[PDB]
Length: 513
Ligand SMILES: CC(=O)N[C@H]1[C@H](OC[C@@H]2COCCO2)O[C@H](CO)[C@@H](O)[C@@H]1O
Image 1: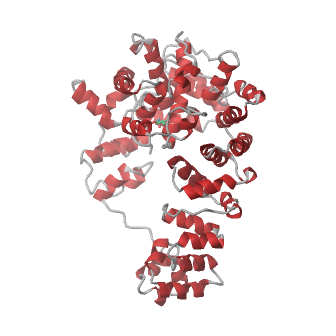
Image 2 (image 1 turned 60 degrees about the horizontal axis):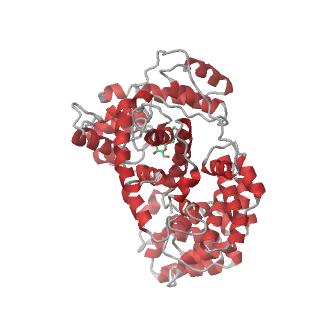
Image 3 (image 1 turned 45 degrees about the vertical axis):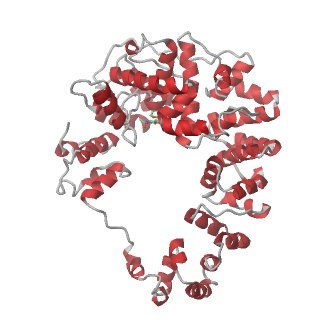
């Protein structure tokens, strides 16, 4: 381990952050050491920020221009100047705290210059501020109220619902209420959004919404708009898949089978149309090694930043330097970027550690590692998940110390490929014994077995139905896990194919119901 003095000489990065966090959790950062430390932190969010703030609370920020505005309370705000009154009324909780006579007075003060404030003040003088704001068709007010409280729910007419998509809050609003199955009046109302007024993710979610109300024609129209507007081919393919499932136009299935993106939808379409499996690149560098230390986390952070900021030309230089057996994961990572994500790279590094597992297990391990880390041994996530299999420290220590009793175990052993694959096998055994399906195992790997069990206990998830199991896959309630499962399933299919242990993705889908 490294002293705070030595860390401070490294460039700011997630690896430096991780090692500062390890000092904080072992109580090795003094109040004096902590003085300058926020300037040494690459991403000052979450656990590292809350640990540091136990040592030095952070005061700010109040823009000094408005400091005086924050000396007033709900009881004294009528004594404040007009600028101070309007600043404090940015807060809906502040508005809710006012007495209703003061809301009446302030609404009159601001009716000319700030009718938005007037609307919210008079809204909070009623028993349902949302109904008042909806009657005014005040769109900014609507989103402010929603952000204040998710509990408001009302029917919204055609005119009002068609205005909502123009506001930056709409995409997260629509996603949250559709996935969480909340706010049913809002959800039903969003059936009347004209597809011409939405695009991309929002259009897609509105398609999903329409399916849940069995409005399949409206669903098709939303999904078609999504397919036409999505920036990523993978997302476009997901929308085309729905267009096909709903209306069964054989041109849509044909377009999906010919996609340049390898994903579950394009793989499925290929299978349904007797189209050959996509071409997988074969990387076999002849050079054995270079000078690069694959076990130095700081060196990875530095080379990653260079690779990500490399122009078309500097990528070619790096490709050559890292075209060795020892740096195969870095080589594939460079090629993936250098080829503009058009070629399919499915490497199997450190294969000696898994070659004695059965091939189905190999493929699941490789599928997870590909998505988690792209096989970078010293990978570190924003939540300080570690190594190729991206173990959280807590689980790493549970397995390495309590279960396996590895002598002198430290969570940094997760950066060793032999350890990553061994622990990954261990945990995947636990999960698969309970969940069976590789998709369910992927959800549980990323999101936990508790979330996965609760999802599978519901009457409306992964049961029989017209559009199952695809619909359920769109309604997995955590976005990171929803995405993750689809990517890991595609990888699994590919690696099973590469290992001469092919399975039809249609058999995976049947086993989800
Ligand atoms: C290194 C890192 O941040 N990995 C992430 C990972 O980030 C994706 C990419 C894949 O290419 C290499 C870098 O990570 O996302 C998954 C969720 O999908 C996380 O569980 C995982 O911890």
